[PDB]
Amino acid sequence: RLRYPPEMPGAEVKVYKKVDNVDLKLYIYKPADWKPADRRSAIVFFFGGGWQSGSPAQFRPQCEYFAGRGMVAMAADYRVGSRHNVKVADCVADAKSAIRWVRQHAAELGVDPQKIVASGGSAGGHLAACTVMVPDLEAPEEDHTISSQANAAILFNPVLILSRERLGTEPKAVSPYHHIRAGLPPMIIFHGTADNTVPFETIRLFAEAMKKAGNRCELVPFEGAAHGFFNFGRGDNLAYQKTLELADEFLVEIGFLAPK
C-alpha cells in the first residue's frame, strides 16, 4: 500500500521546485538506451488524494511501463493540504511548475519539448487537466516564456468541474470545465460509470463540450466500475492492464510513441 514519503527504486530524483523551504521532487524513469541527445516523449504523473494526501508511489507501476516503452516517465510530488499550508490553486501552480521544468530541462532529459504528456488520477487528473487548459495560476517567480502547458493528457477518473474554502480562488478559476475552448491538446479519459466520488456525468458532459469545440477528447467508460478502479492491485489488475493498453494506443495514435 501507498506510503508517504514514497520509495522509488531505480528512479533518478531531481528537485523541480523549491517553495516555502520544501524541495519538491520528480522521480524519473529512463528507458533502455537513453541518451541526452534523444528527443523522446515524456509523461508526468500526478497522484490522487483530494489535494490533501496521496503519494508519488501511486503511479510507479505506470512509470515503469512507459519507460519500458521508450518514454521518459516520471512521478511528481506536489504540495498537499495535510502536509503544507496550501489550497487547490497552489497544487495547480506546482503541477504547472513540473511541466515547465521538464520542458526547460528537455535537452538534458532526452525529451522532445513538444511531446510532454500530463497524467494523473482524481485530484491529480484535475491537475493534469489544469496544465493543458486552465490559464494562469503560475508560480510568480518562474519564467513564463517557457510554457507550462502539456502537449497531451491521460486522465484517470479526474475531477473536471469545481463550478470552496480550500480552493484558493473563485471556483471557476480552478475548474477545467469552465475553460473548454478550441485548439486544446488531445486527451483520453478513463472513468467508472459507478464512481460515487466524481460522478461520471460530469466527465461525459465535459467530453461532449470538448468534442463540440473540435478537440480530441476520448472518454472510455468502465461499466459498473468505482472510483480508483484503474490502480495497480485493484480487482485482478484487469482495468489496470486495460487502461495502459488504451493509453498506449492513444500515445501511438498521436505520434508520441512507436507501435509495439
Image (cartoon, grey):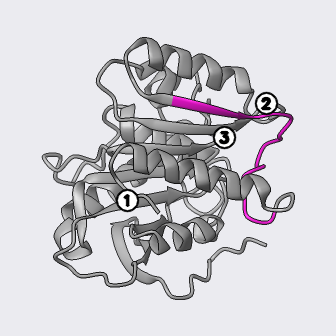
* SS for dot 2: loop
Q: Residues within 10 Å of mark 2 (few under 14, many from 20)?
A: many
- Front-most of 51 and 98? 98
Instruction: Please name the amino acid that badge 3 sits on.
Output: Asn
- Image quadrant assignment for residue 254: top left
Q: Residue furthest bottom?
A: 10
Query: What residue is drawn where x is 60% and y is 54%?
Result: 245
Q: Residue at the far left: name it.
A: 145
The residue that label 2 is drawn on is 193
**At 50% from the left edge and 65% from the top edge, which residue is drawn?**
77
Circle number at residue 157: 3
Question: Foreground residue, 22 or 210?
Answer: 210
Cα–Cα span, label 2 and label 3: 10 Å
**Residue tagged by mark 1?**
258
What is the spatial separation of the Cα atoms under label 3 and label 1, in whole angstroms?
26 Å
Residue occupying the point 29% across, 24% down? 183
Quote the CA–CA distance across marks 2 and 1: 31 Å
Q: What amino acid type should be assigned to the residue bearing mark 1? A: Ala
Q: Tag 1's secondary structure? A: loop
Magenta extent: 218-233
Q: Is residue 258 above or below residue 253?
A: below
For the N terminus, the image quarter is: bottom right
